[PDB]
Image 1 (cartoon, rainbow, N blue to C red):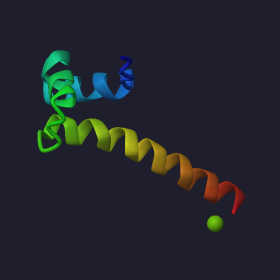
Image 2 (cartoon, helix red, strand yellow; image 1 turned 60 degrees about the vertical axis):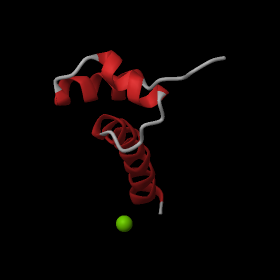
Image 3 (cartoon, helix red, strand yellow; image 1 turned 60 degrees about the horizontal axis):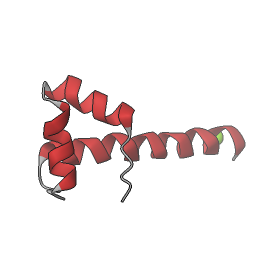
Image 4 (cartoon, rainbow, N blue to C red; image 1 turned 120 degrees about the vertical axis):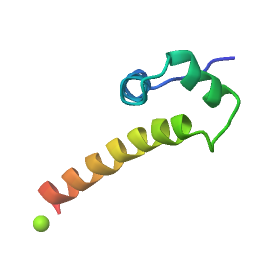
Length: 61
Ligand SMILES: [Mg+2]
């Protein structure tokens, strides 16, 4: 199997939550969506996506 991790989001969660990388990876692996570390990881990725979409719309629409 192959698992993809967003390294930048992982680093940001670890810095902001003062936690180990394995703590984040564990809740992702266990699909424990309710763990705030998982929520934060996906929030960082989702917001990056949304901001990229908004910037595009601002400049081109
Ligand atoms: Mg405008």
